[PDB]
Image 1 (tube, chains in turn yellow, cyan, orange, brown):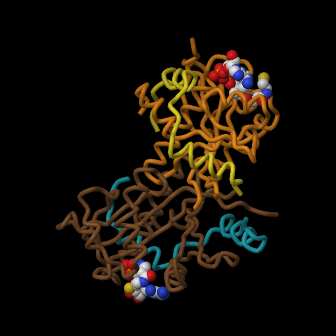
Image 2 (image 1 turned 135 degrees about the vertical axis):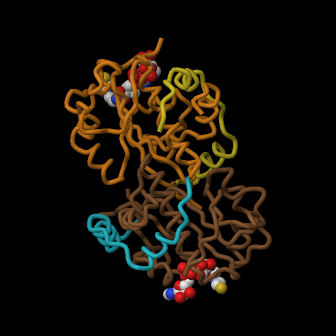
Length: 36
Length: 36
Length: 162
Length: 163
Ligand SMILES: CC(C)(COP(=O)(O)OP(=O)(O)OC[C@H]1O[C@@H](n2cnc3c(N)ncnc32)[C@H](O)[C@@H]1O)[C@@H](O)C(=O)NCCC(=O)NCCS
Ligand SMILES: CC(C)(COP(=O)(O)OP(=O)(O)OC[C@H]1O[C@@H](n2cnc3c(N)ncnc32)[C@H](O)[C@@H]1O)[C@@H](O)C(=O)NCCC(=O)NCCS
């Protein structure tokens, strides 16, 4: 059910993965260290 | 992308789950106790 | 800067589901009517952020499940729901929960596979919020985004949450 | 009765991939050429049954991944994409033990992140028959696919104390 445009996009995003943003990083650092 | 016939069967199998047979049980008892 | 006086647990019997208001009736009603039943069945697991002082008060929740996208198929975990109480929004808790869900799903994926988070956005306001974190909206389904475990892992590794 | 002098590990660099023959070229070549790459990427995780004496000898393997079936009027599952036992070691119950071990691994994940059943890919109808043996129900409209409840699997593992 993925369209050609998206099947290509996703393949590219997965093979060539972006680095994390400042917003994504800030969250990682704020998240308390918890188990499970 | 699941047919009406199968969507009904699966729903029934999941709501009313079979008990394990002797072959499934025998394997469970043989399987060495190990970790993740 | 960010609210951090909370703790994460699986949805349980003692948690105050009725006081939770994120401003969206569906997400409120999901938590109230369906979260625990779905968690018992295994259809979707719901994790709540509880106050460290009032341990029955829910500041927010998220829900996950395994899924695949068919091009070969792509193994993913679906972030089906994420929400923060109106009283607690704009203190970074939403962002922390996206990260925590990423963490949980990556830890599972190490055992049984999965490469990305498939994020369900209800409306375009929520979809915008997710784009903020580097989630890429799909062209053919504009209220669905994808976010690499590579990307998520890099961030969690950076901060020592993995 | 059954072969039980083996132990499970994730596919690794130490494991003798070239000695493995299950009598199927594709499954042999999957283990030899694709298992490790797919395991590194996260597309499918492969677990191997090693001899307790010769810890580099592979008696058998299985591979899993998350997936969902869409109802038409979502079912969260783990796909058992592959299971195989060396020809030298077949007919000693190790195949059965690996189905159970894959069930165990996927159930433990499903406790964290959801999933209700094992979706089993059968290559041919001989293998599909073998799976029916264990209470796996073939889908009508996908004939080489079976479903086996985590409730069913859990009952069996709980019975034996593997959970
Ligand atoms: C809104 C959600 C994500 C709460 O996130 P929370 O505020 O805790 O997250 P966090 O503090 O990390 O981020 C919010 C901050 O991001 C910034 N921001 C940037 N883009 C946006 C955007 N599109 N929408 C909101 N905030 C945004 C703002 O500065 C805001 O203060 C969540 O509760 C939700 O979407 N619930 C559904 C409720 C709904 O759709 N409608 C009611 C809204 S009152
Ligand atoms: C044989 C497989 C399934 C692993 O099973 P394994 O023999 O290790 O397990 P286990 O001993 O529990 O089961 C085999 C026993 O079940 C019974 N059995 C075997 N096949 C069947 C069947 N189709 N239907 C019913 N009972 C069967 C027999 O009594 C046999 O001794 C696996 O290695 C496999 O078949 N791989 C694919 C190879 C292929 O397609 N062709 C080459 C086969 S030589």
